[PDB]
Length: 134
Length: 6
Image (cartoon, rainbow over the protein chains, first blue to last red):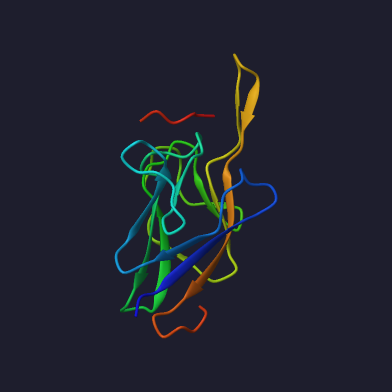
């Protein structure tokens, strides 16, 4: 069986529907574009402050740990409020545990239209292949 | 590309 990540939306997030993402292979977190649209079983979001290739999430069988990696995002990735890498820089793999608060992007105000676009803020639940919560 | 940037 595959490891499983569940992304649930937090109150200060741009709204999204709960995601059930199986981690048979590493999963790209990123912004919706006609080639990839949001689905209940992916980590693609219709959120303008997310990068196209924002981050990667995967399960490592050797360590038994789950990892998140920022892949040169413009606006940042955060675990429990701690940023993974500077803008346009790649982070190392950073361990995530069930219950962690993961943020993709930051709020951005579009100055000419004076509309604030929220970021994605998620509680993540993580399950080992054997079903045990991480 | 195309990201709304702070």
